[PDB]
Length: 31
Length: 31
Length: 31
Ligand SMILES: [Zn+2]
Ligand SMILES: [Zn+2]
Ligand SMILES: [Zn+2]
Image (cartoon, rainbow over all chains, first blue to last red; front, top):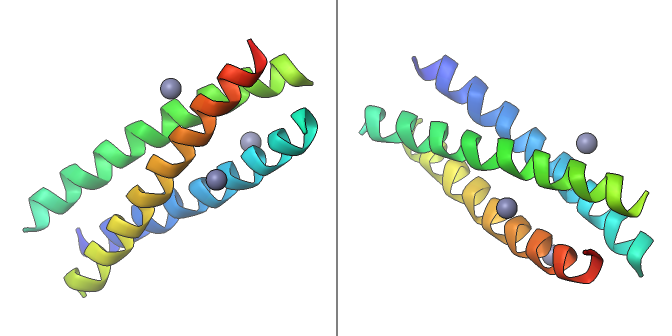
């Protein structure tokens, strides 16, 4: 469960970093 | 504590999934 | 191990809440 938990958390965090970049891109587009 | 953590991680995943959908709709709107 | 995992989950949820706020602010700027 632990490694499975850690794996899911790492995955999620990477999903989050990605969304941060997307949001950064969007802010620049709208200005 | 492990079960509370796993539930928390699931809930976080659900919030992230919703965020992706919001960002996706935004990218469609602004281009 | 669990503690550092809890820390990473809390840091991830903090980024999520922030992103939700950015998304709400974009949505008001777009349509
Ligand atoms: Zn994306
Ligand atoms: Zn939303
Ligand atoms: Zn921000």
